[PDB]
Image (cartoon, coloured by chain):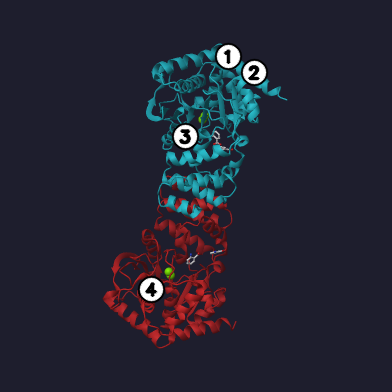
Chain colours: A red, B cyan
Amino acid sequence: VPSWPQILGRLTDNRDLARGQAAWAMDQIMTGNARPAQIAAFAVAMTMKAPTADEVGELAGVMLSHAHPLPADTVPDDAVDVVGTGGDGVNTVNLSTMAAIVVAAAGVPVVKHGNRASGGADTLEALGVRIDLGPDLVARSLAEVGIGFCFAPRFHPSYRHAAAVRAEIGVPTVFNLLGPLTNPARPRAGLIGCAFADLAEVMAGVFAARRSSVLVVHGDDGLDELTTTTTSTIWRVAAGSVDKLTFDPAGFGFARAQLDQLAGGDAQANAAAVRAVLGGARGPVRDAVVLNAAGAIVAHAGLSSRAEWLPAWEEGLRRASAAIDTGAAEQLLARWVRFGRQI
Amino acid sequence: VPSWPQILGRLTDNRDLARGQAAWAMDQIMTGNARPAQIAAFAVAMTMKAPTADEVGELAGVMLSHAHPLPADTVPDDAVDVVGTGGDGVNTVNLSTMAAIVVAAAGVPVVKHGNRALSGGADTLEALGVRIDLGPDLVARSLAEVGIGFCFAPRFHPSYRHAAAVRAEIGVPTVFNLLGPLTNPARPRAGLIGCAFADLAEVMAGVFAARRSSVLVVHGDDGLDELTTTTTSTIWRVAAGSVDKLTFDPAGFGFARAQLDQLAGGDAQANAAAVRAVLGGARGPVRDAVVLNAAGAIVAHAGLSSRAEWLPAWEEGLRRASAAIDTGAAEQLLARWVRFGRQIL
Ligand SMILES: Nc1ccccc1C(=O)O
Ligand SMILES: Nc1ccccc1C(=O)O
Ligand SMILES: Nc1ccccc1C(=O)O
Ligand SMILES: Nc1ccccc1C(=O)O
Ligand SMILES: [Mg+2]
Ligand SMILES: [Mg+2]
Ligand SMILES: [Mg+2]
Ligand SMILES: [Mg+2]
């Protein structure tokens, strides 16, 4: 029976959708069969009717069902993502991009997913990295360099109609959740930042369903990363289940920082901040990077059922600091740049 | 300062808009400055937030400021409308249109707003041979010469085209579905106003209240945007700037309960035939529902005077509506309206 009037009516009636309806809607959007007004009505209605983990999972499933995959056996079983929803309002340095490099340098394979804004892809581009690569070359980068970056428009070309609408309406919706949930390499672990405190649990539910080992993180100051200005909320996903924790990095010797110390402007500035940290500059920015890099490593450790929380953090922090201090992180970036210049 | 992200963000945060924001939005929509996605987002977000009468008033106000007006001093001060939201999802006969003819024949000036839709009011008028395409000047002359005029929504609100398109693309009812009955370009002060959506009728009433109209906003408890004979109706009575909610039972005035299928409509030709049968004096449930709705419009008209009393008003309305059919006045008025249209220019 499925139709726009039926699905929209159910949503405007403040009712959860029936199984399969969110999937039908998203597939319409992804096959160029939904009008801009229909896309917009759906995105808004699905946000104002608080979306469920099942519903958001259906949306992400449809997108992944249409995306370009990586080739068979090119993504190690233990690869990790480090990524956020964005839209925390705060023009920060790209902590996720910095932490990703550090995590890769430490020997954990990283496949990152992202897009232009300031933003993650922009900062990478300004550092000289090729953000643009197709499946076969992203697989090569992962093999040879230890990190890869899937550019969203390259892998999700059928999302362009939905992307054009998000822009036109300019307001956050349920679609802002989809980036971290639709990494086309499908890594099973991640450190995932969520700007929308109310929706982080929903994102966690989605990861739990696919039995990922993920830490979904929201700084109690609003950051879509682990913060050093105060405590963070963590939705810890492992063994298909979610528990909510408060996390205080003071317990690992981290000084309280002020939010303005993690601020960064254009792609050029954030690129300078990356070089500064990877070059060994001390300060609040390094601390944040190390903390979030450790978080990603802890998420990676969680793939093993024998993993323990506090020992995992201590080892993650040691490994993250060493990766920077030895120059490994700095040199991984240099190798990543070199890789892109050599077909 | 005003922008789409600001207004839609406020709405998706479940907040009422600031004074003037809804007006800004509607004006962008009516000037061709809004993308279909923005129109759709706004209509939906406002509906799910729960629109206020201030907000709906602002939307209707912008529309009326862009509409083609009727010439000055051509609409009597006591002219009435008989019109509904539609969207009740039950194909009925054209009760508001039939009632409008009867009310005019009773001597109450009627300027009806309407649209095409099954067969909407405008479709059925066309099938009867009445002109639904007249501009402001000729509608004013219909009113003066025949006692009734019809304002076809698209002809008077051409700048609403972008919004009407989006409404149709998304299908789901929204706050926009309220706007037809609130935006009669002749701006009559009284009306019998149907609302298919029980949860929005009170807000419609509030808008009419703010304008100091004398209106009965009606919702059949069976779902119809008409006063029903099938069961009770909820009526938001608007007079003297204030609204109070009543339940109306036709059994109180001797009407038997009808079944909904007795009121069911068909194509425009079938619905035109149904109008002719009622105006010709056929008894039965359709006549009953027409007389009841014509009476309501006459009660709204009486309400323009603060002297009006509810039960005498309804008894006089019912008398007057019944007599207008029985004397042949209603039938003759329709013939004269058709003739008027055939001899223009
Ligand atoms: N902006 C995007 C994000 C994801 C997929 C496609 C696009 C696109 O622009 O086509
Ligand atoms: N907003 C995002 C965040 C992360 C990855 C992709 C996207 C995207 O725009 O599709
Ligand atoms: N559907 C409407 C509602 C109000 C005013 C005009 C129209 C129209 O279609 O022109
Ligand atoms: N229901 C109406 C009443 C009058 C004018 C237009 C409409 C409309 O919805 O298009
Ligand atoms: Mg991030
Ligand atoms: Mg960030
Ligand atoms: Mg009607
Ligand atoms: Mg009706």
Query: Where residue A37 sits: x, y (%)?
Result: 55, 50
Q: Chain of mark 3?
A: B
Marks 4 and 1: in contact by CB < 8 Å? no
Instruction: Decide which of A313, B324 is in the foreground and name it.
Output: B324
Give above or below for A90 relative to A46: below
Is label 3's Cβ within 8 Å of ligand 8?
yes
**Same chain assignment for discs 4 and 3:** no
Q: Nearer the viewer, mark 3 or mark 2?
A: 2
Label 2 marks which chain's residue?
Answer: B
Crowdedness of circle 3 by 10 Å Cα count: few (<14), some, many (20+)? many
Same chain, labels 3 and 2: yes
Residue with the mark numbered 3: B196
* Residue carrying label 1: B329
Q: What residue is at 50 percent from the left and 53 percent from the top? A: B3
The residue that label 2 is drawn on is B336
Q: State the residue position of label 4.
A: A261
Mark 3, secondary structure of its residue: loop
- Most extreme residue toward the left is A251
User: Which of marks 1 and 3 precedes in the sequence?
Assistant: 3
